[PDB]
Amino acid sequence: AVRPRDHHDYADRIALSAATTDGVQMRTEDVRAWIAERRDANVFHVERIPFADLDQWWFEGVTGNLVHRSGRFFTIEGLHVIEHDGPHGDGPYREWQQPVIRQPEVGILGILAKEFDGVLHFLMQAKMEPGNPNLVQLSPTVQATRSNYNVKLIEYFAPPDPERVIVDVLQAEQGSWFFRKSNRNMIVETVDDVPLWDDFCWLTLGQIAELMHEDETINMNSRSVLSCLPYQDITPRALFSDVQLLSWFTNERSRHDVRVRRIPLADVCGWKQGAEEIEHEDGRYFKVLAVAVKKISWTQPLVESVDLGVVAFLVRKIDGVPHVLVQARVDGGFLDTVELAPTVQCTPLNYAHLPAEEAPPFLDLVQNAPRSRIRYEAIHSEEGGRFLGVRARYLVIDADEAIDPPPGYAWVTPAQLTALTRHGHYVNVEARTLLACINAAAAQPR
Amino acid sequence: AVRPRDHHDYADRIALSAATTDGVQMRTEDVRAWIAERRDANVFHVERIPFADLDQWWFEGVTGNLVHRSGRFFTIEGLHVIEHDGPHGDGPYREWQQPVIRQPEVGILGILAKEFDGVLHFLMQAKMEPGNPNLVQLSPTVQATRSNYNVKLIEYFAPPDPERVIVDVLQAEQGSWFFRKSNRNMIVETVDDVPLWDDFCWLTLGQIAELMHEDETINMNSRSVLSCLPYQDITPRALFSDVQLLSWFTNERSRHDVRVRRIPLADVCGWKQGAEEIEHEDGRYFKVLAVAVKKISWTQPLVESVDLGVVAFLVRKIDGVPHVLVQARVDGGFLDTVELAPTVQCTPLNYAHLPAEEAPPFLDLVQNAPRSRIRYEAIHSEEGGRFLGVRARYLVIDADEAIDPPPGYAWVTPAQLTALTRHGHYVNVEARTLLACINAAAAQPR
Ligand SMILES: Cc1cn([C@H]2C[C@H](O)[C@@H](COP(=O)(O)OP(=O)(O)O[C@H]3O[C@@H](C)[C@H](O)[C@@H](O)[C@H]3O)O2)c(=O)[nH]c1=O
Ligand SMILES: Cc1cn([C@H]2C[C@H](O)[C@@H](COP(=O)(O)OP(=O)(O)O[C@H]3O[C@@H](C)[C@H](O)[C@@H](O)[C@H]3O)O2)c(=O)[nH]c1=O
Ligand SMILES: Cc1cn([C@H]2C[C@H](O)[C@@H](COP(=O)(O)OP(=O)(O)Oc3ccccc3)O2)c(=O)[nH]c1=O
Ligand SMILES: Cc1cn([C@H]2C[C@H](O)[C@@H](COP(=O)(O)OP(=O)(O)Oc3ccccc3)O2)c(=O)[nH]c1=O
């Protein structure tokens, strides 16, 4: 039984869902209320605690790594990075050490899809996570990892029905804070009469697109999985042909010389471990801290950033076809040297001790951009199972003038980014968030 | 200036070249003679020497790694691998230590293409490499690395003309013997009047296809680059749709728990360092040795295998469409856990101390297969800059009965493998060699 290589293309179904905002379950206006209601019904709150009051976590003796005594969950370890300028790397030279999150296991982030009245809906979960700054955001249907093996609906993803897979791909998490970690992003259709429990809501993609314009609503794991949806390209031209884009990126992945090693947390230079936080000696980057989730239900470390981040794509129409200016970013926690990232991705406080000329390219342009050139803006936060209130302004900004890309940057269409999300290690988490925001703004312009 | 995303497709030109065996430069029958002649004109031979007589290599003091004093070239270091069976890995459990080759630099393997009388030719180089068992084989137009910076024609690849790129992709080298190394495989067209020096010959792809049937002729780097050629699929159906194949492989990349670390060579257990070789205590796997290339022109380490290898694809026609049975192989030197590999890939001596039931799946079937089911057979050798006479029987064998793939295996069409070679870390070096052999047998059946 062979089938066409392109069998069961879901692009028309996806497009229909993106165009529809009347969902079977709730009108969109209500969802904030439903969220507000689950936001309100949520019993759990979170308090900062000293490391010593962690239960079942400890700084293990020889490495000083922060680990769970069961071996489950993640660890905080050390990382040393050097980017060489030498005989075989373009540089410039960079060298540092930092804590890093490690968890050498792939988790499942799965969204279940099902047709109602001829239109696909997606089963979103109102989920409390301790680092969400507003506690409850909307997560994938299933968010689970095998070292924890009961999760509702995990049977639809472990293994998925091969006949019903829309998306199934490994995608990397933040390159600055995790060491080489990816999760399996999945979207799978069912025709089954699935149960519906209070924390779940069926939404069309058009409803999700409206919600994607809201601050701190569609959570980071959901935006990563939704960014992988395979829409049909409406304008199948680009400045680089797809071959030229892969050649450009090949050169970017080849031209650096970056050497990374994992080291004991106790060995990390430049960071100070106190009774309540581990922090950089000059107050940059991030802090590791500890929280209790409340009797106490559990305790765990979290990572918090030192400020609000800025993450933006500059957009230009080239012969009528919008392109975004990607950067082939080199981060210490990437598996394969570079990943494509947004035009600007940074926490501005980390550059504030430097002269303006050492700031990331385009940061000033983005920070000064007028409302009249801002095509999309919202504040989103990062995975609340690992990060405490890590927030950034996510922007899409029309560039008023043509820009000759600097080394490391290139004009790419959003459709080329969507195509690359069939594979791992091409599009980084922040760029996947902006791709989902671009797709949302295209489906349901505000 | 935007262009179609599919602009400048070379598939028709490639197909024309594959169908043509009358090349502009030499009829094929002669090339052995030309090779024989360059084989004969070659002055250099190779002698085994004690490690102590290496010039400019040494076992560096603290690590005992074998390194070139200039910092150029590669190193021999140690590797420790554990595959866990535990809470988050399917296993089975494996643990070992071994020497490994490291060179954290991407080299260029480039084939230059040019039309003569309306047909693309490719400029192959008769190149002596010290580990080639017959000294001279045919290499890409340009084989070079930036830590060595004069190489003829390197200007066509550094950087390539974006308007003339046929292939440009990073592909991994052997996972058992190199630590996470890939090289940039490139095919680039020119219309320039290129010089022609005695070590170079223009060949059509049909001529290369005939030569690919010869033992020890088209060298390993050439077969890797040629395997990346993007032919049009003649039968665009398969047992797995392309999405299903990527889902299957995603699960394979997710389901193992393999932890690898680089360690000092001096720390490797189970291997003995003598005055002339480093070897496994039970005579399995490989040896590290040293050679002089001859006054002495240079000296270097080489790795030699303990026996002739066996590398084979089993083939079945499924509804008329031939598929090969790939394995998602876990090797210690892979960057991303698994790569697709041939149905059988092993050195049989490494299993010979074990009962037949512990042998790799299908090895017995392949070793016993009749001539009447062998669709392709040749002996090829591995990169002669790093390996001394490492040879394997490469086979394509028609499977007489249907096979329900065991865990880790799946039926994939050669066209699906060709498509995946646009990206890194999908198709391993031995499978890329067999893909080039399959394409050769299809173009110019013997
Ligand atoms: C963590 C750290 C970084 N560095 C160097 C490494 C980088 O060149 C530079 C910037 O560090 P980064 O962690 O890349 O931060 P950044 O400000 O450039 O980028 C950040 O953007 C935010 C939007 C994301 O939410 C963050 O996850 C992070 O990616 O500082 C140190 O010197 N010491 C350190 O301890
Ligand atoms: C090197 C080594 C391997 N092993 C284990 C690891 C693997 O499970 C098993 C087989 O080792 P491998 O290196 O994978 O060899 P193999 O015989 O399975 O595979 C070989 O096939 C040949 C065709 C290729 O040319 C080789 O490069 C290699 O891939 O032995 C050790 O226990 N100790 C060692 O020192
Ligand atoms: C840290 C931690 C968690 N939990 C509880 C709290 C929560 O009920 C539960 C699961 O926590 P987790 O594995 O963090 O997050 P996901 O479920 O999102 O799993 C995925 C992990 C990675 C990729 C995808 C999913 O364990 C604890 O009880 N103690 C701890 O220290
Ligand atoms: C080991 C070695 C080599 N050479 C000389 C011998 C030869 O003339 C020259 C280049 O040797 P090399 O870098 O090994 O192989 P390529 O040119 O194929 O480079 C690529 C490397 C990796 C990927 C692609 C290409 O240096 C030495 O002089 N001493 C040595 O120890």
Image (spheres, coloured by chain):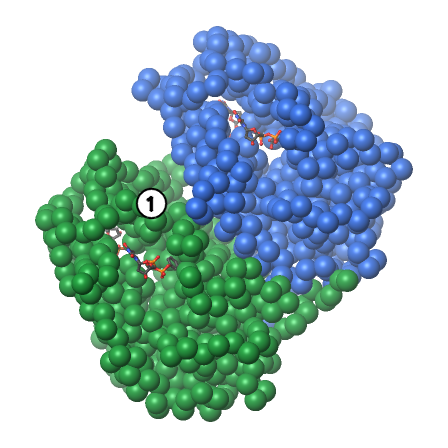
Chain colours: A green, B blue
Question: Disc 1 residue type?
Answer: Gly
Between B122 and A291, the one lying in front of the other is A291
A148 vs B243: above or below: above
B215 on left or right of A28: right
Write down the quadrant of residue A445 in the picture.
bottom left
Residue at 83% of width from left, 41% of height from top?
Answer: B375
Image location (x, y in percent) of residue B24: 79, 44
Per the image, the residue denoted by label 1 is A71
Residue at 23% of width from left, 33% of height from top?
Answer: A62
Image location (x, y in percent) of residue B231: 71, 56
Write down the quadrant of residue A286 in the picture.
bottom left
Image location (x, y in percent) of residue A127: 33, 71
Residue at 28% of width from left, 44% of height from top?
Answer: A69
B429 vs B410: above or below: above
Between A254 and A106, the one lying in front of the other is A106
Quick check: can you spot residue A261?
yes
Q: Callout 1: 10 Å neighbours few (<14), some, many (20+)?
A: few
Q: Secondary structure at mark 1?
A: loop
**Which chain hosts label 1?**
A
